[PDB]
Length: 370
Image 1 (cartoon, rainbow, N blue to C red):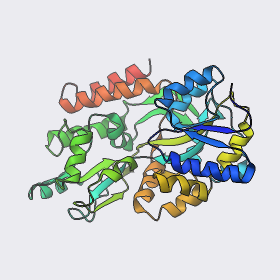
Image 2: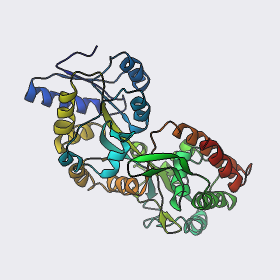
Image 3: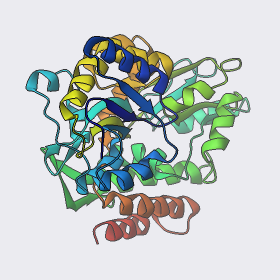
Image 4: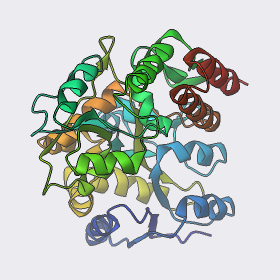
């Protein structure tokens, strides 16, 4: 069972664990309670195994999408932030950590796709998807394309499909409806038709994937890409003077990227739930706590308004949050597993010409609502 009178925290190896460990030392200096930060391999598969026996860390950090399955298994304690604390975080971030109407984790960070552009090719990036064909023709006259981004994974194409009305599952107040899926409605069909038309008109290539697009942008071959905060450190700033901005609109409506919220859950078996609350609310989710983590490895945008408002001096972070507020929290329900694979197939088949847009999306919809 979990040791009383200390905190053990798990966080992934690609996060600022050294900075988190620094917040742990401050907690011990103030309280006398030791905080240990670990980053086990495959921690998101180990956590449900050890937590099922009443073992594991007191606190687990992961993207909120996995916390639905943990919460379905009763692995996470219901958290008890007061309204004053709730007011300190952006409201959509609380939605990411609600399961079956209960808060089951603390939001930490916010990630969403943005439009990334080369300021030397395109100092005024487009506000609309509709003006990309004409920009592409202008840029191709000098051997450059307007836009390359990953077309293989629906995470990357969804912002356009969702713009004029697509959605995965309807979210009312604080609850999903598994019966109301927005994959074959008029908005999704309009957005996927626009994507397919870009391909038919040779403005994009159906085969473009993550690494093809990344290299093209880094080499100065394409004026724009679509990617997230994880990508910024790999941009070749020796070649590219890049900016990051709001995604283009489609039919006048914002693009609606999925939003991922790095969250901190408390193990249901922890005898240290009040220590964990104190650490998370009053040490980590403070300007100084988030600054320690972020200075180590960037979190992107953050859930805490006071620190986000400072971080947003970086226009890349500001754009991340702007796109996230326009976007769709990734649903945490088990039915989302059907969405990913059904919509992946639909987009690949529509882009390749195997299926019409209408048939591709009807099939995807019809699978997700089974």
